Image (spheres, coloured by chain):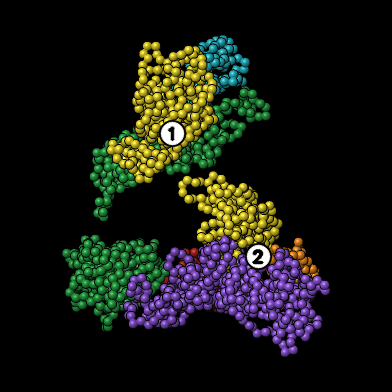
Chain colours: A red, B orange, C cyan, D purple, E yellow, F green
Amino acid sequence: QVQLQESGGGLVQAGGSLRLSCAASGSIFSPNTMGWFRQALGKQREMVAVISSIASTQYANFVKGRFTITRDNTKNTVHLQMNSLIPEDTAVYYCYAVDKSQDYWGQGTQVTVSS
Amino acid sequence: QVQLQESGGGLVQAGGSLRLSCAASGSIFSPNTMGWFRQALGKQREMVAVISSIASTQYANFVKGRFTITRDNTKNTVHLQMNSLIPEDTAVYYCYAVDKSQDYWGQGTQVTVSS
Amino acid sequence: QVQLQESGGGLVQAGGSLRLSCAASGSIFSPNTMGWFRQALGKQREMVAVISSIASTQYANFVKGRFTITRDNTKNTVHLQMNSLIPEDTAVYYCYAVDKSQDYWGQGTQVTVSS
Amino acid sequence: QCVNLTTRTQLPPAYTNSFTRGVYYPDKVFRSSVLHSTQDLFLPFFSNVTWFHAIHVSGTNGTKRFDNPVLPFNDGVYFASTEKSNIIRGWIFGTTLDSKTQSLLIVNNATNVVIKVCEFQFCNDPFLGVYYHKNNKSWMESEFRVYSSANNCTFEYVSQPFLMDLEGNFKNLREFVFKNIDGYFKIYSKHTPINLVRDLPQGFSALEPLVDLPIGINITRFQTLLALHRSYLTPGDSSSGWTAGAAAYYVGYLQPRTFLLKYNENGTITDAVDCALDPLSETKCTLKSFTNFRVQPTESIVRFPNITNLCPFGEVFNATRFASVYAWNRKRISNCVADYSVLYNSASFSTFKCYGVSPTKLNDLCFTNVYADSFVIRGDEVRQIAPGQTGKIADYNYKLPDDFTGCVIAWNSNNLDSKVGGNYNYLYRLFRKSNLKPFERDISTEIYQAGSTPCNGVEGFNCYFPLQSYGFQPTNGVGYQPYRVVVLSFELLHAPATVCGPKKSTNLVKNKCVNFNFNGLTGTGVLTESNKKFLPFQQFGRDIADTTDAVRDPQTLEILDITPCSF
Amino acid sequence: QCVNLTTRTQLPPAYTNSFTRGVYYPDKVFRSSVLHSTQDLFLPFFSNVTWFHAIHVSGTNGTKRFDNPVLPFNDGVYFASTEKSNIIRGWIFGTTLDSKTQSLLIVNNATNVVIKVCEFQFCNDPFLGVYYHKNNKSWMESEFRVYSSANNCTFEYVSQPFLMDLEGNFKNLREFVFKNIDGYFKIYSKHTPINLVRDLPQGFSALEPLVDLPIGINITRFQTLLALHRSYLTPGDSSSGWTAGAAAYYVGYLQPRTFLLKYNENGTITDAVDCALDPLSETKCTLKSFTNFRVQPTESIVRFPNITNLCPFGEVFNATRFASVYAWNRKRISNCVADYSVLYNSASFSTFKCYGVSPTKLNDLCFTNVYADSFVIRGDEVRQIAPGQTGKIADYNYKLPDDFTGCVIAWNSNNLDSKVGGNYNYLYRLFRKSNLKPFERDISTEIYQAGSTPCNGVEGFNCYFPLQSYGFQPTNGVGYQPYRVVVLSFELLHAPATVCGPKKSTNLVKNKCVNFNFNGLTGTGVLTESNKKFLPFQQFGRDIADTTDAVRDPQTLEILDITPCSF
Amino acid sequence: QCVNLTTRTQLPPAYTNSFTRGVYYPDKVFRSSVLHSTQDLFLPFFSNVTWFHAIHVSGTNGTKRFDNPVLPFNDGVYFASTEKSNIIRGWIFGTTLDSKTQSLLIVNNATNVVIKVCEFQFCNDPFLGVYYHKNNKSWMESEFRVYSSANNCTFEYVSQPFLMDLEGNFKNLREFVFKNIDGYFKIYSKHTPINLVRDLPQGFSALEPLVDLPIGINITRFQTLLALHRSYLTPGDSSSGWTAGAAAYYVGYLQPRTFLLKYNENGTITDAVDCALDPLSETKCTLKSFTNFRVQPTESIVRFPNITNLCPFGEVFNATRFASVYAWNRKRISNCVADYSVLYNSASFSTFKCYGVSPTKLNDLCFTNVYADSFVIRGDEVRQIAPGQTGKIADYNYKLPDDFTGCVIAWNSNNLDSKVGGNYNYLYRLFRKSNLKPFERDISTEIYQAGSTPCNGVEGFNCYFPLQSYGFQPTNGVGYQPYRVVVLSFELLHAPATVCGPKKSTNLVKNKCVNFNFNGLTGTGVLTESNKKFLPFQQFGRDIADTTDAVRDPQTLEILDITPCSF
């Protein structure tokens, strides 16, 4: 049972910063690929960003220059720094474990930004 | 020259009924097998139904319980009663006289059903 | 070994006459073809003329109406009468035995015309 | 036209003995003073042949009616007639004896024969009405009331009459053998005067060939044509017919027998010996002169070891979760028993596309390795899982090389993967740089460059992520519904097999001659309980080194010794 | 250059006897004191060899002309020459002896041999003008006048002279044997001093091998080159030539014979026995030591019935329409003449596969019947119409029995049977409950069960109609193109033939040993009038059941009994 | 994870004797009181088996190092272990024993057996670190240090322990036989208590089958897995290990042998006889009870006639003058010996391309005719002499048909054909009316008509001579340098050959059994000097007419008589 634990969201005023964390347990074979996905009520999963074991980082044009992904090789965990927050970022986010086999999703982290 | 006379088609609104007729004339050796086949523009000869001299009736799944074939032993003719017509039955139909070895072929009857 | 003897050249003041000669010995099968070629220092072998066994005579356009080939069937030899000589004819001339097989050239005859 | 007679009332059968009658010349070769052994359809000696009166008077009033039943035609028929007044006229042969199947009619009037192969519509009581002329009475005029109509005639024959004129105890015996072999109707005949013998006479007369017709039809039943000299409109009290049916006809059925025929000096068959009649006749045939074989096993026994190592197909087909369409779940199956019947017979799935192998002999084939691919797809795209096909899945997802051996099986999965809000956990690429190679698994997430500018892992103008998600919902149409798909690719190589089919065993019969199959060792014999002790690693026994005297049954470990069935 | 001589005037031939001459060593094997039997091309003993004078004076005036004719070269030559002055100089071998074909020339001057093979232009009278020098006279200079021209020379050979110098009754016998076997020209020779014997001497001298030239040309004729000592311009009255041609040469022709050669202790052949000469020699060869076959048939008799109708192949092969491969069209062919050259040589068909009969001999066989089957099949499945084969067509549609006798004819039919939309009037089965028996034809349309549930005449889940259509389109590949197929199964039984080839009946000779053919029965024997009576259905006779002692002539109904020609 | 041990230092081998050990049950067949002869892989009796100490103490200091050298696996292995402390734990089998190839591991912990087949990355010194628990000491916990990584596992097996627990002179002997046949790894085993016998005991114990694993991998070498009871980090001075390796294991290699096995009444093997051991054993196997073959030739001799003739390639390849490319030099080559090694191996020729024939077999092959074509061409055009090629020289000069058999070989003649002033003796056409046919030679000098007006043998406007000259100069570039080219076209026809490669002959060995090849006849026998005399044309001897008793040596003319090698 591969489990993805996500945390670090909540309500933040416009211009604030948040720090999400997502830790993978279970099988999670070495050539893994952790991604973060966005969805607002009424829309589809918006693929926020993607990182592989190559250490490459791939970001979408929606949040250019604003969100970053950090790795912890020792615990093989992933962390999003979400800075310069906008009301357009009001959306629940999920983890996507590409791995090599059966993909695993998270439980969700609410991120609210409004004034 | 064994000839297959086909008649009784045309334009009928959805839900109507028709009665096609095939008369086989000439040699038409006694242990025969009379069949009807379907062809829509762009599609295949869909084997609709087959009756042998044993009086057994054989029908495909496309028109379950809707089309019936009756036989006339005196003239050795065949009639297709086509009821509960659906636009999916819009196709030109043909007769297949299996006979003994010389398998013959009809001229065709246009059957159109739409609203 | 097929040998071609060439003789009769030298120094002649412009307007004089000479009679060069090729004699062919060796195999020289009956259907042979004898031609003479020109070479001045700095140029290539320009075909002077050709006689076949048919007695046909073919000459180049450079020396129109001035040079003539005579045949001797008894000895199967050939003589070029070089008349109406010009400074432009200053070149060593060589023989070519086309024959039917491996071809053989002459040793050369210096012909110089100047004033 | 035909005339309806009365009901035949199903008279009980009556039999008589055939004292060595019905021997015909089998070949067209002259042999003199030689004994020849021929295996052919002969009427067995001293057999029971069923005899019918032409006219039977069995009613209390004195009712007179033809005994003309439709009789079977089993591999030929021996038909004999004892008569004196030409009341038997011919026969009709066929299967259905109507306008549905071709029929052969042979009839003899006073002048010649009429042989037809047509589509006769025979009535229930075909017959010939016979009337004399008022002044001559030398010949009999016949009105045919045999068939209502005749069509599709493919044969015709006329020749000298089969039955001579019989125009008072000068009874005559006419014997015929009818055979229907290789599209040929062969008739053999013989005529012999008889005297004071009611039944078949004791003696020997060979039937010389009469004719070979290339009619080439199917015959299963036959009938007899009889003539009424009497009147059907007005039946007389008595004597209107011919002396209450004194004449009669006997029918027997040929069987494949080996006969020894004796050709004498003039070339005529004088005597015959039926090799299966007695032990005596058997000796005569064996010596070709006129002057353990007992036990055969009836049932078969197959005993194979238990089917234990079973496939985790339940972990594949009954799995709760199927991997995304770009992480294809490929699982090894080996070293275990494979029951494909459970899946095929259940047929709860929607597809069984089995290529290079028929789906019903999968249980009979033990393969080297099995690859089981598990996922969910849309129904309209299910058609794309087969070799040589194209499409988004077939070209970009999972290419099936044109030379597949294996099965694709998909079933409806609407109530399992779909949710009300849409299940978008199943991701699907629509763009790639190139098509795949077969069985390639690409799980890269690189953003594809639709334009001329590089994307550098960032979407934008002419830059798109590879995977779009699927709107699996319980209200979606059949084409848009989820479909659980498993592909079993089976490996048939020059390597030992690890996945075998459910070897089915049977019951065990002891102390009886039986065909047995123990662990692939096949044989025929009787089995008994033995007091031998086998070492645990030993399976068979060979005390004489060339026959297996003992065996150990795979299921129950007792040791059964094999006695040859031939005593 | 050549010089024309006078006409030879066709001198009458003269013969002499060859008393055991011409035996050569057939091998290079040293055998010592042994008797070896060899079957090779030898000159038969005591044969007539034809002998020609070198110079013949037959005219009244006293003309001297060379006797130099062109002679045949029949499987080798034995050329012997009795001479004393070296007038014979060599030979020329070839077919046409001109520039069209290659020729071999062997000449001997005083010094060496000249062996050439070129496209040689020989004149009518080849010779060598021989003249002595004015002072020495030890050797004779030779001016060839053999050929006008020589071209395409493919062989040159020089060695020590075949002929020794002969420069007064010291005659010498020079014997040569020439063979032309397997492209090799083999020359054997032997030289013996002779004394006071005009003809071939009586004695034995074996010919030692001399040369094997890998010549590789075709030889049919040969000639002899002679030496002209006199002058052709001025012929002398007499003595200008050499004593009016006392020297001469004898020619004999080798034949295939079996000889017994006796190799003595030193390895040389000392004696030989010609097995076919006299019965004593036959005996010697039988014992391999030195201390019915009389009647053969000369004429052949062919007898066949009066039949003129032509077998309707055109209604089968040139037919407009052909049946489906589950409704197999069988047509019976009988009572007509069948010309199979029309079919075999037409070459329109692709498959000519004949089993039990060679395809070139159908015109030479007569059969009881022919069965012609018409088909429309794929290209790829054409390989399935043959005995012993498997596959959808060969298993479910038509089986040829493993002992099938007849010819399967396969030819393509794109421009006849394919249509642009695909011709779909040809139905073939993909499924059946069980396999067929040979020549079985099931035309059932019953919907098959694929699962465990019954179909009840209705398709569905695991229920399919048997019949599928075929995409015959003019753009399809060769494997997918239509091929019209006819199978001719021939019935060869002990029954009279109805289908006959294009043969010719001949006359009947009696009481003579002859090759006979009655109604297809071929044999060799003598025929006599028989008192046997054949019943009208009988055609052959076999009193001993393994040889046909009697037969009925087809034209005249008389019965002729056959006695084996061997006594 | 693995730990690197010290260097093995390549201890010298030590041997011991195997007194009738290693007989296993070859089959699973119960035979009682019978003597069965089986041909299979057995360990030969009284063989030398190589024995290793598990721990060897050979250094002066007293170092303890495990002894387990990677050993071959030659068609099976007999592995015996005499031990008392379970220090031997398993084996590894494979070809490379790395991640490249698949490998099999069998290991035994205190509980069960682990059998894996994976792509293990074996370290140099696999073992298991064994440590007891602080309180119980009943079992020993094992830490495997065998492989770095395992991938692509295709097998798995667990069962009851191969080696029993051994937890003080109660030594035990465990014998195993490993075979790898038909993809199956077969293990046979037996355990016996031993007493006071250091080496293999004398006696008989049959090995009962243990497992048949369908591993299906290739096996070439194997190694032993040992238990490390001491600590690698701190090696003790003494006694840290197990009594300095008193336990040991012995390895022998199976060989194909025939054995006579004696099954007693209960079905167990109680004795055996090795048929190849001693003549007594051979006799026992011959009688199947317990109570010229000597000379074989060692070398081969080939003798052929010398290469007296020589093909004049030198007048072709070392010729002073080469013809122009439009009067090509064809010379016919026949009746000579062709040595193609002189040309092929000369190391001074630009190219060696042979079409239809390999150039290394040229001397071995014999050619009917060889056509040698000699000329000089330009470098960049050398690529145009090969079939199917185009270009001015390939299309206009000398066409080579697509089906060549022959060789094109040309070299640069820079120092031979070039002059300072330029060599224009080699004349070249650029224009013709049409392309040639292959091997066509046109030497016409007719002026070509480039325009529409006729030239009439005179140049001018659109009229050019056919031939332009070549500027061969010693300063020209490699593409513009002269190249001497010869094309050797070979004729393989059904005609006798005139050219053969120098037949390779060898030395002669007399008075010894040899394989000989004289003049094409091969045989096996011994050769002696013979006093027989052959006629000069005779080559062989056959006194009994079926065997070649004598032969003539081709090089030296002595006559050697051949005695059969079998006395």
Left or right side of B71 for D351: left
Q: Position of residue D234 (x, y in %)?
A: 80, 82
Identify which amino acid the numbered label 2 is placed on: Val
Q: Is residue F316 above or below residue D462?
A: above
**Residue drawn 35% across and 45% down?**
E287
Circle 1 residue: E47
Q: Position of residue E253 (x, y in %)?
A: 45, 33
- In the rendered image, the residue lying farthest to the right is D134
Q: Which mark identifies residue D211?
A: 2
Per the image, label 1 sits on a secondary structure element best described as strand
The residue nearer to you, when weighing F309 against F223, is: F309
Identify which amino acid the numbered label 1 is placed on: Ser
Q: Chain of mark 2?
A: D
Q: Position of residue E151 (x, y in %)?
A: 50, 27
The residue nearer to you, when weighing C97 against E288, is: E288
Task: Report whether residue D284 is seen.
Answer: yes
Q: Quadrant of residue E320?
A: bottom right
Q: Chain of mark 1?
A: E
